[PDB]
Image: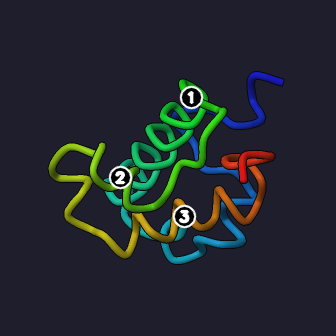
Amino acid sequence: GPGSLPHDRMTSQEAACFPDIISGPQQTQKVFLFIRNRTLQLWLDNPKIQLTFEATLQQLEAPYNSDTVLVHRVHSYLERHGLINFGIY
């Protein structure tokens, strides 16, 4: 339901892949959440073509585009778990 993937809280599936983030300072949790939310919004605005890591990074404003390792992790997590890029190859 509405609680499953809220904009303002990390989930347990995310916790398994980001234990360092969910355990850590709140402001870095907010960075994670912004990246996740924007990546999903980019995908769902155009779910008929592949959303790549590079395209995501180019569409994130500063300062979110600065931590390229974190953006890559979020994008990889979302794609590997099927939340982006289903059916578009």
Of the image marks 3 and 1, the number of the one nearer the N terminus = 3
Instruction: Tell me the quarter of the image containing the C terminus.
Output: bottom right
The residue located at (33%, 55%) in the rendering is 57
Residue beneath label 2, please?
31
Amino acid at dot 1? Asn
Amino acid at dot 2? Val
Percent position (x, y) of residue 70? 40, 69
Of the image marks 3 and 2, the number of the one nearer the N terminus = 3
The span from disc 3 to disc 2 (Cα, nearest Å) is: 11 Å
Residue beneath label 3, please?
22
Residue 20 as seen in the image, left or right of residue 62: right
Percent position (x, y) of residue 2? 75, 22
Indicate which label's residue lies in the foreground, 3 or 2.
Answer: 2
Label of residue 63 in the image: none
Indicate the secondary structure of the residue bearing disc 2.
helix
Instruction: Tell me the quarter of the image containing the N terminus.
Output: top right
The residue located at (48%, 68%) in the rendering is 21
Percent position (x, y) of residue 27? 31, 54
Label of residue 46 in the image: 1
Amino acid at dot 3? Ile
Of the image marks 2 and 1, the number of the one nearer the N terminus = 2
The span from disc 3 to disc 1 (Cα, nearest Å) is: 29 Å
Indicate the secondary structure of the residue bearing disc 1.
loop
Eyeballing the image, is 2 above or below 9?
above
Indicate the secondary structure of the residue bearing disc 3.
helix
